[PDB]
Length: 209
Image (cartoon, rainbow, N blue to C red):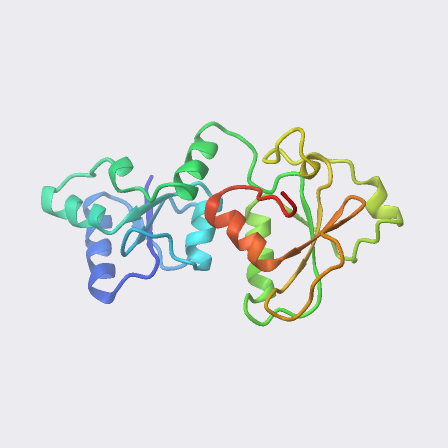
């Protein structure tokens, strides 16, 4: 059961996607949800949008619009792999096909302070879609909740500190804040750009190394 959505597509391109969905006996959404299977972008790059990033975290096909043109011209569902955006999207799709944990499984996040460039609610949607859990109180390395969390992060290397230091205080960068150190106890301080870069590459990126 296919469910198509466009991200960054022109009006003409959206019309073609709608026409393709009919031919494929698929649905075409305009709002993302977890039943989406195919996200179509206009060119060779993942768009830096909530839809594309939710598509990555769901393991969707992220495909160049040439796939749509080829499907309509040849009147078949062309094989997705030839049109897939490489790196993050493919790594995530393969991750989902192998039934592996989501990118931020085992990780906990506290969204600290003001967010002007990345609406906080978008970060919450993303980290939740990626298997992360929200902390409602700021972690203090010397406190009750943060000393009792003992999860592991599947997408960290087993020998890295991110394997077992799985709590993240997220702050908005480009706002003149620089933590003295990136980690205190089990708690990292990470900029919102780190979070975005993780999703776009489908990697739990290091904050030190």
